Image: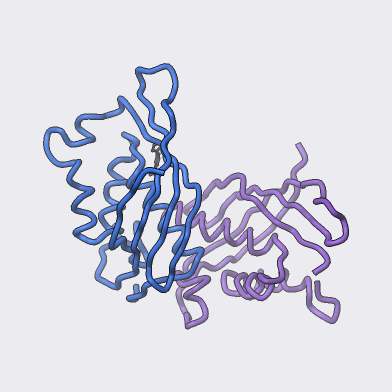
Chain colours: A blue, B purple
Amino acid sequence: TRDQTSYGDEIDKFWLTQYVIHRESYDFYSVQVDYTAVGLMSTPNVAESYQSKFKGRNGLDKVLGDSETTRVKINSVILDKPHGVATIRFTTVRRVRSNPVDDQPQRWIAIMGYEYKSLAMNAEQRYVNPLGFRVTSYRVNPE
Amino acid sequence: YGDEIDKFWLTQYVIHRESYDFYSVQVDYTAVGLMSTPNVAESYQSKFKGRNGLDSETTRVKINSVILDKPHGVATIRFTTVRRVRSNPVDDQPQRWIAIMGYEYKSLAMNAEQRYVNPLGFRVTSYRVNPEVN
Ligand SMILES: O=C(O)c1cc(-n2cccc2)ccn1
């Protein structure tokens, strides 16, 4: 909509958490929806390193299928609105359909830079991102 | 504009209206004033209208469900509240409720005011809330 670094605590918090759930979760049924969302909510450079694991024969969706899944769980969010910086602590629970039960959960820390860029958008894009939220920097490290 | 985007303003609205706070009384009253129509918003202010407007107590909320009815702009939110007076050293016994509301997206007038709370023009048309006891 409008060039803007921040939209408030609650607004930024929703877009940030949604992003992590889209990009760190893997469900064979929603992969296309998750894939499309991360692209629109990211700069080309940020979207490039994520789309890489999906290209070619050994693309994640081509290899995994529905043999496994990873669930995502948000645990806390720290906003630095004036700088467009945000820290996110979350948990991920993987599974494989051939094992008895789930495997041990994994704690992560996400350091994200975000903004709201005003640019042209098509109909199918108005559904994904209204305020034009975009991640300009992303990297996760173990807890 | 999608389920998640709608569920956000809805749950936030239920949290805004069905709660009670003072740091946030200057932020919740103002918040609901923008996410509501002049028709369904006077039933919410009517609670302080006059001299006897509503620190001695508090009321917090936790969302437990969302179900959506897209084509109509309605939702079936189910939440719980907890009352607490400054005096009583412990919280009150929880109570469970049910609500359905009307929302729309009509960005007719928007200023410096709504960017923080409501820049997407989320507006509530209808409201009701009724309890639930098994
Ligand atoms: O990213 C989503 O919004 C999502 C994730 C999942 N999911 C469940 C386990 C792992 C990913 C299912 C449906 N939607």
Look at 51% across and 57% down and name the residue there. Answer: B8
Percent position (x, y) of residue A58? 15, 33
Looking at the image, residue A141 lies above or below residue A6: above
Q: Nearer the viewer, residue A18 or B32?
A: A18
* Direction from residue A118 to residue B48 in the image, left or right: right
Q: Which residue occupies the extreme left position in the image?
A: A56
Above or below — where is A59 with respect to A126?
Answer: above
| Outermost front residue | A143
Which residue is at the far right?
B87
**A123 up-or-down from A3: above or below:** above
Identify the image quadrant of the C terminus of chain A.
top left
In the rendered image, is residue B1 in sight? Answer: no
Which x, y percent locates residue A99?
Answer: 38, 18
For the point 20% across and 47% down, the residue is A51
Quadrant of the displayed image that contains ligand 1: top left
Q: Position of residue A21 (x, y in %)?
A: 39, 46
Quadrant in which residue B20 is drawn: bottom right
Q: For the N terminus of chain A, which image quadrant?
A: bottom left
Q: Determine which quarter of the picture holds residue B2.
A: bottom left
Image quadrant where residue A57 sits: top left
Residue sitting at x 26%, y 63%: A122
Residue A125 placement, left or right of A80: left
Q: Total of numbered circles in the picture?
A: 0
Which residue is depicted at the point 77% across and 61% down?
B58
Given residues B62 and A82, the one toward you in this image is: A82
Q: Does any portion of residue A26 appear in the rendered image? A: yes
Q: Position of residue B67 (x, y in %)?
A: 55, 46
